[PDB]
Amino acid sequence: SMSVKKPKRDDSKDLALCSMILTEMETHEDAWPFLLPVNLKLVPGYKKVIKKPMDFSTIREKLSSGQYPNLETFALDVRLVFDNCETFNEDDSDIGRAGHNMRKYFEKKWTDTFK
């Protein structure tokens, strides 16, 4: 509350560490469905169904231009990529499986880096 603060967690490395995580996600072999925005002209249904499209390139640009106020807003966009993927793709599809694998991969790196 006013004049009463928890001890200051060092957040000065967060930008760099989120960048490294994002690099590792970008270079994973199963990243291919997620590297670029879904083409809303060429994929029937996507525009109407997925209210908040997100992809790794868009996260990378937001990261690089100071549009994440903290590491939680960064994790929310990453998870949005996988939540969207589950909304639109069957679990038993190459893309559906990619999304589960990438989410697992991300969540481990997240825990190991920050928790």
Image: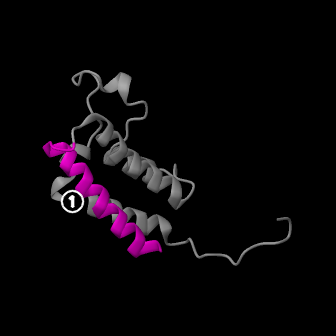
User: Looking at the image, can residue 23 be seen?
Assistant: no
Where residue 35 sits: x, y (%)? Answer: 25, 46
* Membership of 111 in magenta stretch: yes
On-image quarter of the N terminus: bottom right
Q: Mark 1 points at which residue?
A: 27
Color encoding of the figure: one colour
Secondary structure, mark 1, is: helix
Q: Residues within 10 Å of mark 1 (few under 14, many from 20)?
A: few
Left/right of residue 13 with respect to residue 87 in the rendered view: right
Count of picture labels: 1
Q: Which residue lies furthest to the right in this view?
A: 2
State whether the magenta stretch is mostly helix, strand or loop.
Answer: helix
User: Looking at the image, can residue 73 be seen?
Assistant: yes
- The span shown in magenta is 91-115
Pick whichever, 19 or 77, lies toward us: 77
Q: In this view, does 92 lie above or below 17?
A: above
Where residue 3 sits: x, y (%)? Answer: 85, 70
Q: Quadrant of residue 7?
A: bottom right
Q: In this view, does 7 lie above or below 44?
A: below
Where residue 28 sits: x, y (%)? Answer: 20, 59
Q: Quadrant of residue 52?
A: top left
Where residue 106 sits: x, y (%)? Answer: 33, 62
Q: Which residue is drawn at 30% across and 27% down?
A: 46
User: What's the amino acid at mark 1?
Assistant: Thr
* Membership of 2 in magenta stretch: no
Pick whichever, 76 or 20, lies toward us: 76
Left/right of residue 10 with respect to residue 84 in the rendered view: right
Q: Which residue is drawn at 36% across and 44% down?
A: 83
Q: Which residue is drawn at 40% across and 45% down?
A: 80
Left/right of residue 60 with respect to residue 7 in the rendered view: left
